[PDB]
Image (cartoon, coloured by chain):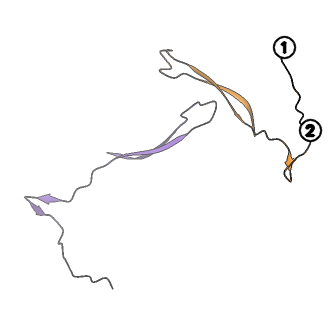
Chain colours: A purple, B orange
Amino acid sequence: AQRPQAGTEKSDIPALNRRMTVGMDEIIGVKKAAFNGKQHGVVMGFFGAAGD
Amino acid sequence: AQRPQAGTEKSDIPALNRRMTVGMDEIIGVKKAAFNGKQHGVVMGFFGAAGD
């Protein structure tokens, strides 16, 4: 919905540069494809990894 | 480190001039000259002032 955009602000007094804030903002949504209660394109697999 | 500088701000709404703040800022350091635990150029003297 919105690409990440940046912006800055002079907070306390713009003449007496005592404070400044930078920031970034985003509108996005991520979801796994699901139809009729089923995974659309993923096969999950569980294996025993010992981690030695 | 910084001479005293002044600045102003329109706080609440810049259109509806309901509030304003002025201010002044400074960076400075003051210290008596001391070398090897001794006063460099002062001789302190204590006298009895009655204050009548």
The residue furthest bottom is: A52
| Chain name for mark 1 | B
Q: Is residue A44 left or right of residue A28?
A: left
Q: Kindly state the secondary structure of the residue where label 1 is placed.
A: loop
Question: According to the image, label 2 marks what residue?
Answer: B43
| Amino acid beneath label 2 | Val
Mark whose residue sits in front, 2 or 1: 1
Q: Residue B41's spot in the image, x, y percent?
A: 92, 41
Q: Position of residue B48 (x, y in %)?
A: 87, 26
Residue B52: give its label. 1
Q: As drawn, is A44 to the left or to the right of A9?
A: left
Distance of label 2 from label 1 (alpha carbons): 26 Å
Counting residues from the start of the chain, the first of labels 2 and 1 encountered is 2
Q: Quadrant of residue A20?
A: top right
At horizontal 63% and vertical 25% (from top left) the residue drawn is B23
- Helix, strand or loop for disc 2: loop
Q: Position of residue B40 (x, y in %)?
A: 90, 45
